Amino acid sequence: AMRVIDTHCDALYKLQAGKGKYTFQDAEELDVNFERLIEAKMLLQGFAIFLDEDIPVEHKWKKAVEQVNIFKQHVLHKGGIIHHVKKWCDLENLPEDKIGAMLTLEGIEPIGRDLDKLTQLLDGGVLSVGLTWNNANLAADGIMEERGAGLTRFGKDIIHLLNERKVFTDVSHLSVKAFWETLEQAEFVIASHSSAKAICAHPRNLDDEQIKAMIEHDAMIHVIFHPLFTTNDGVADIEDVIRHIDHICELGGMKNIGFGSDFDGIPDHVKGLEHAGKYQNFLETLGKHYTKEEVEGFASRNFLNHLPK
Amino acid sequence: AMRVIDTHCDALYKLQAGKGKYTFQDAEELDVNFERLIEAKMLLQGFAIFLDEDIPVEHKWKKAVEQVNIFKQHVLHKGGIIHHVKKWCDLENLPEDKIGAMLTLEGIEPIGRDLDKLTQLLDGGVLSVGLTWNNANLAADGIMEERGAGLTRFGKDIIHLLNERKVFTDVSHLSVKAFWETLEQAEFVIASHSSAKAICAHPRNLDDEQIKAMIEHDAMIHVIFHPLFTTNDGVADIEDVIRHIDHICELGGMKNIGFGSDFDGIPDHVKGLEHAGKYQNFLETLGKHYTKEEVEGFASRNFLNHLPK
Ligand SMILES: [Zn+2]
Ligand SMILES: [Zn+2]
Ligand SMILES: [Zn+2]
Ligand SMILES: [Zn+2]
Image (cartoon, rainbow over all chains, first blue to last red; front, side, top):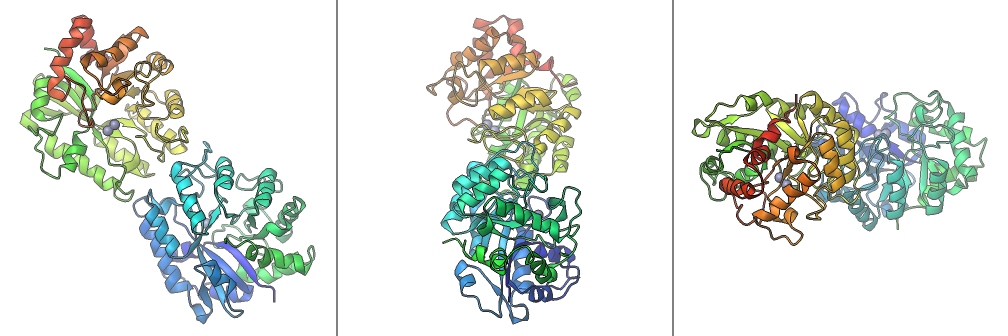
């Protein structure tokens, strides 16, 4: 039984937007639903808290908390199997029949200038935080901001707290400058859903020096199943995804690769990776390029070897 | 009788903080109150919209609308004499017995990332906009942010809107980088309350190169009545303020100088200038140093030669 850790899906965002017309148990419009987790044989799934950039700055904090309660009410205890991983020890002591679920924060927009709002979310079980989504915010510039500046003092204050609380600092949407400053400050670095710039040149992807630095830093790179970041022409199959894994391995990152699908946040899908239920198929295909020992590394063992401590 | 244009006071912030306790007509706590505007022979006073940095992000818009309402309800029409300058033509056509009052925005924090909220403020009469106060925000870094970055996409979009609406872009608290990028983007530039760094080396002040650039751009520099920005030692009298005026004149900016007191935002005052009712005393001292025609330039004519058109 090849169990799977996936670091990033947008199920919370989709449920929230759905206004009840979607049930987490079996909605077919959700790449990540309860049935599809079982079928994926998930060990752990990360659920991102993420608000539309058009949610007014003064409603952000309320809508975030709402997504959290959607998690607590809809996702948790589903079928008596979904278990809340609120701390890394909850993960290391999870049963074989239970599936772990954790919360992650995709941009700090919901917290304004307030570190107590962040502390609240951390007390709620948030185990990974990305300072930015695509845009400039109070902590740093995201990757689509042309200015591409690094961290503010507020940003550094945030990371200092993440370090203190054994929470991942997620660089996936971070500007190039922010990424580098973050590596300097953060103790536990992850890229929750990124691929390799050398294979697909989207600004969102990691260049070779950044990948080497991640490896050197002992950080995790979780490759994304989004075709816009997989191939330059934006149309991709499973083999295309594998070419990104190949690239990171050739840079020496065999032990630093995991999966970060970005399921439910995908406008278009990779052929054969249409939803979390297609996971074991993906692993079988992967298994023609990598030993089972290596695939298990990508699937869960690398991540489990990199828990904040 | 020489009339006075002053581009910047914090009466709205004080009024709001006073929680109804301060009457605009004559409160001693208000550096700019009605009786003192009369004594000053004010022609036009700028009223800044400014929130404590500690106001949570989700309440900023509300607190700002509060200040606009304070302006409309406590300031306008007082004595049948205070007249709303909502557009520049209201200023050039002010009836003889009237005193003009205009709104300005001291940092774009209250609008979140919503350009429409800015459009509302502009429609309500904001005629000058500083992108930042001291801190990083969604538009640019302020002068006290270590990162010291320039304009974001949002900041550039704001300036385009200000250009189109014939509104001043105010660089008084902008980071050095943001200052230079703003001179590039903004059609109508002002420093609503800033002095000369060569005289007083505070980081908020303008160095000779910046001043020469302001003059070249045909921008207005309004000298401040804050001791902290007036003398290196923080203790100042009227003659100390005049040194800044002299300095700018020497750089060739006699026609680009006006006044920006920052009254009501000053913990300790320039001796002799403790409130707006001392303004004529100020002009009397200027008159030792400059012809009457030159003093009228600083007091109002210069600003009146620089209205956005
Ligand atoms: Zn997302
Ligand atoms: Zn995303
Ligand atoms: Zn102010
Ligand atoms: Zn100020």
